[PDB]
Amino acid sequence: AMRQCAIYGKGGIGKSTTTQNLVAALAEMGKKVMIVGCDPKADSTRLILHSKAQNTIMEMAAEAGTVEDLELEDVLKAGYGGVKCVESGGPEPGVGCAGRGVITAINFLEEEGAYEDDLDFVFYDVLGDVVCGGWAMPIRENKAQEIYIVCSGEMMAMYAANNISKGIVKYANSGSVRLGGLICNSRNTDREDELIIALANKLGTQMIHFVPRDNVVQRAEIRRMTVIEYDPKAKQADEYRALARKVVDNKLLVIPNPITMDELEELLMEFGIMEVEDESIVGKTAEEV
Amino acid sequence: AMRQCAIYGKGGIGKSTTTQNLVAALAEMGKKVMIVGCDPKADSTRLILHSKAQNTIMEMAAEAGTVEDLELEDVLKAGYGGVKCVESGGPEPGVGCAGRGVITAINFLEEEGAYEDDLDFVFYDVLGDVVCGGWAMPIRENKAQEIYIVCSGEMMAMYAANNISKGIVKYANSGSVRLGGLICNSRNTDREDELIIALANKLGTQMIHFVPRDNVVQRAEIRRMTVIEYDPKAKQADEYRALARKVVDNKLLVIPNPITMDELEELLMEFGIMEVEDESIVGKTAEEV
Ligand SMILES: Nc1ncnc2c1ncn2[C@@H]1O[C@H](COP(=O)(O)OP(=O)(O)O)[C@@H](O)[C@H]1O
Ligand SMILES: Nc1ncnc2c1ncn2[C@@H]1O[C@H](COP(=O)(O)OP(=O)(O)O)[C@@H](O)[C@H]1O
Ligand code: SF4
Ligand SMILES: [Mg+2]
Ligand SMILES: [Mg+2]
């Protein structure tokens, strides 16, 4: 039953709100789930807990002396729908790797009955604009079974997406690290979905869902909760549920193959995002061109 | 004469365009400068060179076998105004630290007559949203004399700015790492400058300059050059020159002192960016509230 799924993507796109709401929808349809948080903040777990900031492990690393002294309650709590939030908080900002802190955090959960439960899914909210060895270390482990990239039809959300997929390449042979799909969290740029679908199959995956930009998200988040439990009757709530439907029923999980930057550049030149740069004007001043 | 200055900031704000244009203005007023690039791309050096992508060191690390075999020409070139561009390119995406690659790149320049020249300034274009030990490693060295944070009146450009400053704290005692100023690269949100000035003195520095969002930047960058050499007669060109004026004449260089997230949250609640969240509605459903 238990599948270990990572929610990768550039910082800012929609990871935390998407994942918390997906899981809420998933939990509404009877699935037992755990949410793991890796952002250098407590925001990734928040909406389920209704807490301003959940207590991170890195934060309780010094506030216990030794990490070994902590329990399951003080580090992880289940809020709405019995879905278990836990935050890492890597790093202590300026010295050390973010991801090496993340890794020792799951290793805590690895030597306790956290994973070993009647659980179906575990979700790893984590960034990857730049996917360095540090931020690519649950893929070193086999914590990264199913990888889903939240992105949008914009240069760097997408550049990031291709680079998260460059990291599946490296560890693809040595373990079950797969790319499940692509989530397009809407910017509202016209034929955005289309662009993420072009890029989806350019990479070999599909764009499993297109999440809209509904303002109800904002109304639910000032009550520090998910849209799922704020108004289940909301249109976006069923959009979020729809995602969870495709997640559980997902059978397409491929090892991707990245594209060159020229291939990403021409893709955005096709869809009209990037400019039709004249090579005749490059390197020249305004009084001539 | 030689001051070693870093241009820190969140990914996307304006680092590459700001720095290349600052240096171009600086070089127009007779200063000999070197531009160092650390973004996982060649974009940070581009506009001076007019090249689509400059040849990075990490890229020529395998395309030479041993890093020791490379020269000053194949790794660094001077484009317009004799200002010397060099790109690192860290990392090989998925394994290893970005910043540890950056460090060994400057160490190349450290054992060649790159620094030791008739140079006045060196500029380190580098990110810091999350400032980890890896991305905080020219501050471990004394490559980070003068740190200038490009940001805007928005949650994470600013969150980042405070966190770059949290990293000056750590290495402040053990070397000359200072915070020179704050550059506000305009979003156009109304009283944005004001917000970066509030945050500037909340941190102890000043907001040395307010860079506008002029579309001429776009017209100069399709000719893959700086606005300085595209149209010197442009209004934004003098804005960029103005920055360089304050840079050289800068005397204010402090060790900052970060603020709590509540202090950043209330600052944005004062300036109207963040919401006036009702505590009476938190944790409750729509049919009641
Ligand atoms: N589908 C959406 N519709 C509307 N707003 C959204 C949506 N997804 C995310 N957001 C907005 O983006 C903000 C930040 O999202 P988050 O997921 O926390 O970012 P990040 O990628 O860092 O984890 C949300 O709190 C909200 O302001
Ligand atoms: N002063 C400016 N006026 C207008 N656009 C700007 C300005 N500075 C930066 N930009 C825009 O921001 C884009 C990205 O800037 P860049 O400096 O490359 O970002 P980053 O902080 O990652 O290094 C620029 O190519 C341009 O689209
Ligand atoms: S760049 Fe990556 S590997 Fe290097 S310190 Fe940062 S999180 Fe760790
Ligand atoms: Mg987040
Ligand atoms: Mg850049």
Image: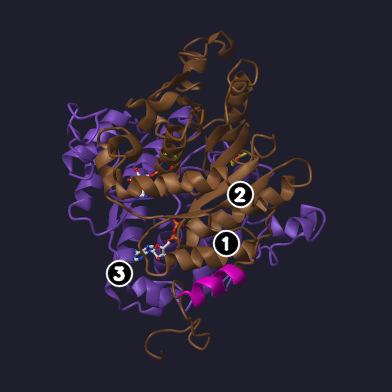
Chain colours: A brown, B purple
Q: Amino acid at mark 1?
A: Ala
Q: Position of residue A280 (x, y in %)?
A: 51, 89
Specify the principal SS of the magenta part: helix
Q: Position of residue A17 (x, y in %)?
A: 40, 41
Circle 2: is it few (<14), some (14-19), or many (20+) Cα within 10 Å? many
Q: Position of residue A125 (x, y in %)?
A: 50, 38
Q: Nearer the viewer, residue B173 or B150?
A: B150
Q: Which residue is mark 1?
A: A200
Between discs 1 and 2, the one toward the N terminus? 2
Q: Which residue is mark 3?
A: B214
Marks 1 and 2 sit apart, C-alpha to C-alpha, by: 11 Å
Q: Which residue is mark 2?
A: A180
Q: Residue at x 45, y 52 (%)?
A: B11
Q: Quarter holding the N terminus of chain A?
A: top right
Q: Nearer the viewer, residue A112 or A2?
A: A2
Q: Are marks 3 and 2 in contact (CB under 8 Å)?
A: no
